[PDB]
Image 1 (spheres, rainbow, N blue to C red):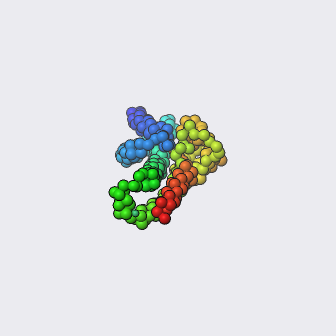
Image 2 (cartoon, rainbow, N blue to C red; image 1 turned 180 degrees about the horizontal axis):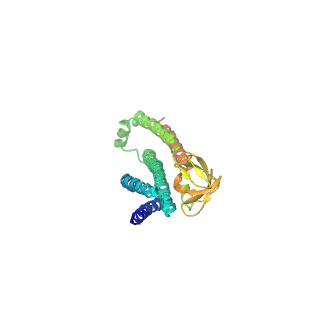
Image 3 (cartoon, rainbow, N blue to C red; image 1 turned 90 degrees about the vertical axis):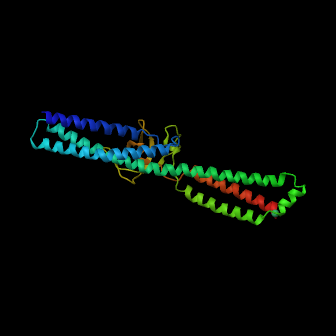
Length: 271
Ligand SMILES: [Ca+2]
């Protein structure tokens, strides 16, 4: 009857919406290439608001279904089926949200870290340039000599020390930066990758729990990875590629070496 048809109709609309959002989030680019983290943050926030309202509608639908179940239909089976589909997709939606939380956090941190690395190397280049001017340019004119006398080398040395400390801070931060490059399908695998599960995934072949430590095996169908918990194909969004990021750590080491060279140069010029 009209009662049932309205239920099936309404449940189909909600299932359409959820399936739409799922396809958006699964096939989302959480890799090196995608930089617009602020836009993702805004979008995600908006999705959240949509879900807070949607919760009420879906709870209403579940109730409407339960009502229909009291009077045994020949349509009971497909009603129970739709009820289960709503519960399942609804929960999986929230789990996808857990993935978004984790990815926004770690990814924002990744971009921020590398930006800070660029900022630091910049200032080291400025320093090197200054020193090169001290030992290359003509210090003959009395103006230049007076400038040197007016210059506090001890203050320059304290600047250098402070910078050593900053660099140490960066080295520490690099030990916790995730891997974003190994997420793109255009990445060469020279071995298996460590994966950290950031949500609950649940199916016949495999069940993944939040925090489960897994191994990446290789690309499956778009947006999916064949991984090892039991081996199976899971949506790439369920996983962080945890530290260590060797690019990051080696970057900070490169900085420390360049800085040590500059300090040595400074001491050679001043003592
Ligand atoms: Ca001086």
